[PDB]
Amino acid sequence: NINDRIKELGTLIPKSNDRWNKGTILKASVDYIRKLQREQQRAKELENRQKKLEHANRHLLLRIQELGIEDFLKVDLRVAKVLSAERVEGSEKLLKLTLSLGDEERTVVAGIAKYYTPEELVGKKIVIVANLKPRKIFGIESQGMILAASDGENLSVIVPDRDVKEGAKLSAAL
Amino acid sequence: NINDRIKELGTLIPNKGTILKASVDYIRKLQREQQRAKELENRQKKLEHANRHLLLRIQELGIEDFLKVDLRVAKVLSAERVEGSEKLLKLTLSLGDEERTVVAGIAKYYTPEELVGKKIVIVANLKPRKIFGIESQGMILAASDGENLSVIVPDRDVKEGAKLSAAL
């Protein structure tokens, strides 16, 4: 009832290595508590610095990843229209896209051959990066590049919600 | 003292058996919450590394951003006030190799007579911006305090078109 609980306090209290009375085993208790009280309060004050540092770290990712208008304007995203698509012989991954920006016709290469059929591409309004650097592929020049979104399993080209005249430049204005 | 110091345990936690039994609970609780702090004290060890890596990255990012700016000394060749505007000055500037044209908004703070001839620091790479009829290839550095506008000039004399460099 009482002595067992005081004896229990003896178990939780660290090794005394000293007399086993009743008051002594109770004295250490208020000592133990007071110390633990001090520790947690010092640790609790420390945690506030960690959170203050937590946000501070995040806020530094924003700063380092910030885009800016002018940097963005250097990237020219425009809606295109597919004219034809043919599978490349000797490759089960590449498709040669013929695109229409209204005025300029472009030749792009895409890896969606497994995920996309030429028949379903013709007529589709896909978004591309026109400015993007040509990378010679299979002895063929890929003028501009195609935007994609991949989970690894699922491949997806990008499309405007409504239909729009081919060639429209994507803006972030208002 | 036994009862009085037990009573002290009453002031500790925010009937003799009740608070005694309420003490072991406070103990067991504290014996857990402290065991966590030792992990959170090692958590904040990794967050110390994070701040370290990001700053050095920002530092490198900061230095890289500076070298993008090609600060070059130019020499005013002409200065004529723009017509219909009381704030603009079209300035022809020799850099020693090619004479660029630059508009400056320092009309109210300067006379063309006092200006012409002085070797001033400008921003070279700055994109050419057309300002009502003139194609300014770069822009000039001017300090403003609200009371005084001041163009920027090297302390000693140096060859025109010199590349203003910071140390590193």
Image: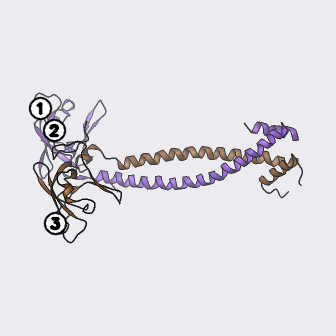
Chain colours: A brown, B purple
Residues at discs 3 and 2 both on one chain: no
Residue B12 screen position, x and y as percent: 75, 39
Q: Label 3: which residue? A: A140
Q: Pointer 1: residues within 10 angstroms few (<14), some, or many (20+)? A: some
Dot 3 falls on a residue whose secondary structure is loop
Q: Label 2: which residue? A: B103
Tell which tag, 3 or 2, sits nearer the viewer. Answer: 3
Task: Kindly identify the amino acid type of the residue bearing the numbered disc 3.
Answer: Ile
Dot 2 falls on a residue whose secondary structure is strand
The answer for how far apart the CA atoms under marks 1 and 3 are is: 54 Å
Q: Pointer 3: residues within 10 angstroms few (<14), some, or many (20+)? A: few
Dot 1 falls on a residue whose secondary structure is loop
Q: Chain of mark 3?
A: A
Can residue B160 be seen? no
Tell which tag, 1 or 3, sits nearer the viewer. Answer: 3
Q: Is residue B28 above or below residue B104?
A: below
Residues at discs 1 and 2 both on one chain: yes
